[PDB]
RNA sequence: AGGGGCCAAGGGUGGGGGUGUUCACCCAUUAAAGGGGAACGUGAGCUGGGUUUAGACCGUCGUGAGACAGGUCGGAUGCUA
RNA sequence: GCAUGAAUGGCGUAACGAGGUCCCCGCUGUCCCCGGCCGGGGCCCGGCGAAACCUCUGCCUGGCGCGCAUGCCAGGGACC
RNA sequence: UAAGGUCCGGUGGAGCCGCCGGUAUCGCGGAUCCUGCCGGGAGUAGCAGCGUAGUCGGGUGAGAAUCCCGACCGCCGGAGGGGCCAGGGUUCCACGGCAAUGGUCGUCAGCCGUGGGUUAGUCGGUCCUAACCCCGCCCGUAACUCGGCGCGGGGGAAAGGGAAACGGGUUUAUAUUCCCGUACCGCGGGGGUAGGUGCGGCAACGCAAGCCCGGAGGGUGACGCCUCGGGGUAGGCGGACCGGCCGAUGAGGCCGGCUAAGCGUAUAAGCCCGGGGAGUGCCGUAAUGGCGAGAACCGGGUGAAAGCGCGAAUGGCCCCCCCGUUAGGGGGGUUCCGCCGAUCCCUGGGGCCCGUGAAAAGCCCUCCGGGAAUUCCGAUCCCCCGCGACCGUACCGAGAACCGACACAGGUGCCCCUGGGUGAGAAGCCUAAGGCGUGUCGGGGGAAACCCGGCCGAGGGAACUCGGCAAACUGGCCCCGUAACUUCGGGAGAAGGGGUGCCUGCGGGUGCGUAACCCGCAGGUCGCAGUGACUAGGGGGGCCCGACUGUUUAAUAAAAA
RNA sequence: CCCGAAACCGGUCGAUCUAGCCCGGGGCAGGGUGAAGUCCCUCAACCGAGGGAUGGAGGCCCGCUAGGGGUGCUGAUGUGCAGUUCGCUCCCGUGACCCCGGGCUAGGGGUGAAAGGCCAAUCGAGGCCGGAGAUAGCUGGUUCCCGCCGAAUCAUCCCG
RNA sequence: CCGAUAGCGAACUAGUACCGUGAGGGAAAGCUGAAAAGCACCCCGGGAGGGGGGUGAAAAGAGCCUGAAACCGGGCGGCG
RNA sequence: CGAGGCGCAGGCAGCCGUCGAACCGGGGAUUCCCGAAUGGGACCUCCCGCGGCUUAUGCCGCACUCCGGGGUUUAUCCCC
């Protein structure tokens, strides 16, 4: 099917997805150069996981 | 559908939509012949149907009128001869 | 098994190891029902050892 | 030194050496809670089946107190034969009675060794025990090996012979058909020889075909060294 | 920018035809570019800017002439043949065919009264036993006997 | 037509049959079918049959593991200067 | 029989084998003896772009020397 | 002497010396040192080898061989296409871009940025239980997060078992789920009537079921192997009619012509039942074979698929003639007859056996019936009111989303295995639906040497070499004929020899009436060659070893082991 | 002084690789040969003889069906496409066959049609951690300068 | 005592990124300036790229204090 | 403590605070799911047997294993 996620696993996948953003520009102003790179960036292909 | 392998509950009829899409459907397996069991013979006046279908169908099909619908009339043809001999003595 | 490693390796596909209900590391082996890291399923206790492993992360945390 | 041997694996009860118990069929019980004396008990052959792991045919019997149990099938049984259990069972084939109640010089099988333990003796295809002599003290019965064991007279047994004779009269034919039989039973196979097994694998025999030390082994020899002709009294076929 | 890659897939589902069959007018690329919706694609279908190629069919002429010729006993000499003898015609299958008529034949005759209950047994039984070639032969052999002929 | 000796390397000094064979044995030719050296010329050229891996067999030896320049089948030939 | 031999199996064997060895017929560039062709590389251009490894370097021959030298010694060749 | 000290200039823009006494994780050239940074190699190799693909106009943009549109030229054809399990995890979809990423460019994208999307009473999970597992308890152990038994309970298949649903429509993205239509599960009411808790028929048997808590029992759930035959229809193709098209001549060809799940009413070989009564004993099947424990033969009954109608004038195909910057539309007509040939699917026989081939949930029946019954009762019959606890659904599923660090020529399950031509064929080639030209770097030198794939070589016919290794030859099919040996089964497709095309005209078989195929025969005739292509065994003999088939050092040894 | 290996041992962690064992499923174009079994005709008193049919078995054959294996080319590659690949050729291809999912067996243990093979790029005893900075008579290295003196490479003993 | 190739695994986004089926293994990554004035306005450029002018001082102009060596371009001297 | 704050984190925007914030101490409220995880199983989710209560949804309290005491058909079964 689907497969075939468990509800929770989708919660976890969703979280990893959240971590896989790019910071916003304004924080960056607030910082005035700065913590960047966002360090977690996870690529779907590039990386695994956990499950 | 979700079953791919041609497993037993899987088995297939071709179905047409008019869309001309032509999609595969599963079919329910075709009926095994209930036995007398007291002597092995397929039973007259006893249905064939799919074991699910018998739930939502009629009971008339599921028996003959004579006692022990499960066994054949001739095997009952033994059993009464015995029952009386048993009441007599 | 030896070489021809590319030819071989279609399993791993199946998973036997996860984020654990108890610890959260990547070792709750679905098949055994045992976490390699924490020891959940196997024991009431957390896995901890003289060598250690578990301890090392904790000290490191301090 | 070398690994545990082929026999030592067996003993573990590990699964290559574990009998299936889920494709295999019932065991014999005669049941002594309704006793032999003050009998009550006849039954009807409900069906006859082949038991895979006995390599013999076996009977399901429907008793008239309402219990269903298997009894090892006699030759020349019909489905709807009545089998009786007790001493006041008729003296005929397939009927079960105590040894004392059974005549001398009649063929008998399924003999008890402790009264009321359900048959622990003569339960193979086509072979049979002979009642040679009977005395109220002890009844001596002659076993399939030619060898006489004394049993209590209040053991049960069934009159007749076992069914499924000729069993080794027909051959096994090929390695395929044989493979098929061993799955039906349990018997570690294909089984090779120790002689071209390496010195690690097995106590006797090296790289090439020749035995190490003598094949013939002690009766006080170790586990894992008790292979070959075990405690052989003689060997060969000559003076 | 200017997609159009989806718009083709979408058009494909509305038209219920293959992607490869879609014809977009070359003069009207700009108009299809501004097509975002299916409803737009549907407009463009009516205006004749989005069309379907015709589905081909392989010609059977060449088959037909062969089929007629093979129906007529031709193109089947020892030099066109590719399978072994039984292969064209299954030796069990033909026989399975052969015997049923010999039996129908006798059966027809059983109702007609021509042959007594007394000949038929020998004949029917003879048919299982392969004496008859068949229809012509059965007719001949009984005719020789006399009882058929009556 | 030889035997034996001197000068002389300019040129020539082969083809096959057995053998893993350098050697050697033989055949028919040939004018003659010479010898030796070059990492026992020549594997960042080939070939890889043999010698001396890991599989196996026989004989001998050895209690046995196991061995043999005894016999024997099989057993990879890397690199962009 | 340097140093065979009977269930540490002897002998023999139809059928069978991507097994070892030998012969014959057909066939055939394996060979006498190589040519031409074709397509992909090679080779050039444009864009893209690594590695192995790295004391140095225009030698050759002899002698010597750790006895198997571009570099010592003596000649010769020597423009990049 | 020197280890090292000191001064000037430039740079730099806050800390720093000397002496004396102390102290040490105290001085670096090597450690196939360790780490970090960097050059040559190179602007070289790779960006080729596998069935070798693009190309012209035009659109867009700063920039176009590789983005898009059309035309034109190809590959693919059980897959380079379609649907999916695992697994991945937003890769999906839209808009805006190109610094990086993509074996090259890039205006594209799977990258970057920013937004958005997976909706379920009737699909599956969930339930059952398997092989098997765990827990408590009993016990062991010095003891346990250890250990096997015996009890008692609980768990165990997203391809077993199993309640019930399809079609059409719509979305940028989802849909059997949202919508529309039609259908229906479970439970819970209500209202009627069969029902003095069913009437009516000799019988083989009739449906508008059988009041009821309870437990019991019994069938069906329910299972190994392979033929053959019987049925179903997905569906391939000729003829005829209706439109669309292409078009020397206006022919022939291409194309659209469809009917769902759910119901109602019908299934019928198996299998029973009456009548009758086995004469040299008869009869049947494709076949083995049945019969006096009921034949031959006549009437019945009885249980898979299948047809028709409902579902459905619809809807969905297919055209025509008008409205136009546009939007939203309108009116029309066709939407058909047969006969014929097939995978599979379902149903009987039958052959097999030193595998004799799990359970239960659930149904259906029956035994008993705790009680309620005549002011009655009950609802399997109808019809009708209400409701649906929970998780999953995107996309991919692959010679770029999996796994191999790589978008790796690898290799991992199913299903479409019956598209047309071919031909024994799920074979090759070609070709249709469908997909693609991103198995992602281009261009040039007629391109010489050399190297890989491959083609052809006179004469000679293994002289090569350890060795005919490699390669060649035979070749499909039909006919003839067929040795030694032999475990009589085989050897054997021995060997060797002949034939095979097209056309024109016949005959046979099966059937029904000229269908659908198949098997022969004669004449005429062309080529070098008729399996002309593709497909497609070289043969023969002695000897050694091992009986064979199988297995073996997964990855230098497949053998005699 | 510093570094340097093959071990050994103790406690742990793997059967998603792979081996066998078990449950429950699935896959395998087409073609050949033709056994038992059964039938008939003609000819014979019988003994049998000749012919033809029907049926359909096989650890069976052919086969580049799918799928499994991997013989030769000692070819192509050999800083690969690939840490075990490619094409032709070749073996098997209804089976002692292949395959999926579940489930079992763990390190002197398992498993093995048994090669010392296999048990997750690691097997004549896996991996991880600890003992552990093991210890080696053995290789390599051991860094500022200057001044002064300046060797022995012999003897006896020693599992040396 | 050490002082960012050092000292705690880790001066920080650390037990992170990442590896491994798992047990377990495991980095690197500190410095603007007085003030952010963190680059307006003007010229150029397809241009988010880059150059001139604009700060006490930009070898203080965005991992921005200093700013070595290897090494790379150009230029000067010399050789060629 | 007391006159600015709104964590690391200098942005933009807006906000709060004398009826005294931020902050510090003490006390209190809320404190998901999994976890010894205790009703049962699980791949961090799901199902279920009682009893209380609101008309219903909602909501509140409970049933693994010892010891101590009860209840009763003394089912060793259930309750504090």
Image (tube, coloured by chain):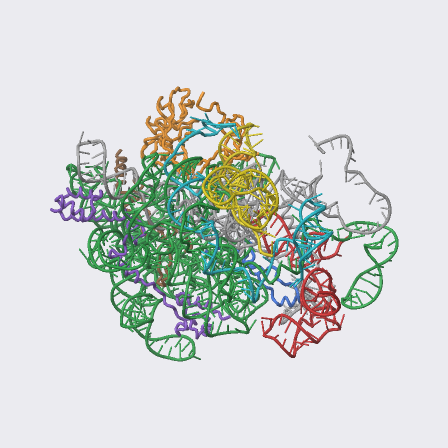
Chain colours: A blue, B brown, D orange, E purple, F yellow, G cyan, H green, J red
Give the side of residue B32 with respect to residue A31, left or right: left
| Relative vertical location of residue D203 with respect to residue H117 in this rendering, above or below | above
Quarter of the picture containing the N terminus of chain A is bottom left
Q: Position of residue H37 (x, y in %)?
A: 67, 59
- Tell me which corner region of the image, top left, top right, bottom left or bottom right, holds residue H547: top left
Give the side of residue C31 with respect to residue D156, left or right: right
| Relative vertical location of residue H179 with respect to residue H535 in this rendering, above or below | below
Give the side of residue D131 with respect to residue F60, left or right: left
Viewer can see residue A43:
yes
Between B67 and H324, the one lying in front of the other is H324
| Relative vertical location of residue B34 with respect to residue E44 in this rendering, above or below | above
Residue at x-position 35% and y-position 60%: B16
Q: Position of residue H373 (x, y in %)?
A: 32, 49
- Tell me which corner region of the image, top left, top right, bottom left or bottom right, holds residue D181: top left
Viewer can see residue C14:
no
Give the side of residue D156 with respect to residue E130, left or right: right
Between H386 and B70, the one lying in front of the other is B70
Residue at x-position 36% and y-position 23%: D101
């Amino acid at each position: 099917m689907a497969r075939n996620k468990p509800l929770a696993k989708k919660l976890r996948l969703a979280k990893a997805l959240k971590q896989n953003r790019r910071v916003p520009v304004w924080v960056i102003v607030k910082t005035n150069r700065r913590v960047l790179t966002h360090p977690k960036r996870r690529y779907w292909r590039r990386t695994k996981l956990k499950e | 559908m979700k079953p791919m392998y041609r497993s037993r509950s899987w088995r297939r009829k071709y179905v047409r939509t008019p869309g001309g899409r032509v999609v595969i459907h599963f079919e329910r397996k075709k009926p095994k012949i209930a036995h007398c069991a007291m002597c092995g013979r397929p039973l007259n006046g006893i249905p064939r149907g799919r074991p699910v279908e018998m739930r939502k169908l009629p009971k008339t099909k599921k028996r003959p009128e004579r006692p022990m619908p499960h066994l054949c009339p001739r095997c009952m043809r033994k059993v009464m001869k015995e029952q009386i001999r048993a009441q007599l003595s | 098994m030896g070489s021809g490693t590319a030819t071989f390796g279609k399993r791993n596909s199946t998973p036997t190891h996860i984020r654990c209900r108890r610890c959260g590391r990547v070792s709750y082996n679905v098949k055994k029902g045992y976490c390699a890291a924490c020891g959940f399923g196997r024991s009431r206790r957390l896995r901890k050892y003289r060598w250690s492993k578990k301890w090392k992360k904790k000290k490191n945390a301090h | 030194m070398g690994k545990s041997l082929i026999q030592q694996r067996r003993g573990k009860g590990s699964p290559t050496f574990k009998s299936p118990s889920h494709r295999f069929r019932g065991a014999v019980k005669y049941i002594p809670l309704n006793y032999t004396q003050e009998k009550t008990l006849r039954g009807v052959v409900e069906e006859i089946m082949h038991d895979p792991g006995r390599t013999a045919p076996v009977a399901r019997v429907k008793f008239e107190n309402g219990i269903e149990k298997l009894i090892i099938a006699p030759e020349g049984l019909l489905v709807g034969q009545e089998i009786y259990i007790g001493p006041d069972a008729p003296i005929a084939v397939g009927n079960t009675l105590p040894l004392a109640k059974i005549p001398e010089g009649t063929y008998v099988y399924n003999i008890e060794g402790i009264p009321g333990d359900g048959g622990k003796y003569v339960r193979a295809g086509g072979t049979y025990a002979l009642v040679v002599s009977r005395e109220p003290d002890k009844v001596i019965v002659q076993l399939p090996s030619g060898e006489l064991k004394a049993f209590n007279p209040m053991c049960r047994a069934t009159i007749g012979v076992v069914a499924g004779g000729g069993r080794l009269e027909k051959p096994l034919v090929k390695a395929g058909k044989a493979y098929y039989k061993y799955k039906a039973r349990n018997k570690f196979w294909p089984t090779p020889r120790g002689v071209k097994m390496n010195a690690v694998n097995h106590p006797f025999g090296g790289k090439e075909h020749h035995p190490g030390k003598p094949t013939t082994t002690s009766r006080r020899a170790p586990p894992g060294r008790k292979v070959g002709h075990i405690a052989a009294r003689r060997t060969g076929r000559r003076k | 920018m200017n997609t159009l890659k989806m718009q083709r897939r979408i058009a494909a589902e509305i038209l219920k035809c293959g992607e490869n069959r879609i014809w977009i007018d070359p003069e009207r690329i700009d108009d299809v570019a501004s097509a975002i919706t299916r409803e737009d694609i549907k407009r463009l279908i009516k205006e004749g800017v989005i069309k379907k190629k015709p589905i081909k069919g392989q010609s059977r002429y060449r088959a037909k002439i062969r089929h007629e010729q093979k129906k007529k006993g031709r193109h089947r000499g020892p030099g066109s043949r590719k399978g072994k003898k039984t292969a064209r015609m299954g030796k069990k299958e033909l026989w399975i065919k052969t015997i049923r008529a010999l039996r129908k034949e006798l059966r027809k005759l059983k109702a007609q009264k021509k042959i007594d209950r007394k000949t038929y047994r020998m004949l029917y039984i003879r048919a299982k036993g392969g004496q008859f070639k068949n229809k012509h032969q059965l007719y001949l052999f009984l005719e020789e006997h006399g009882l058929l002929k009556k």
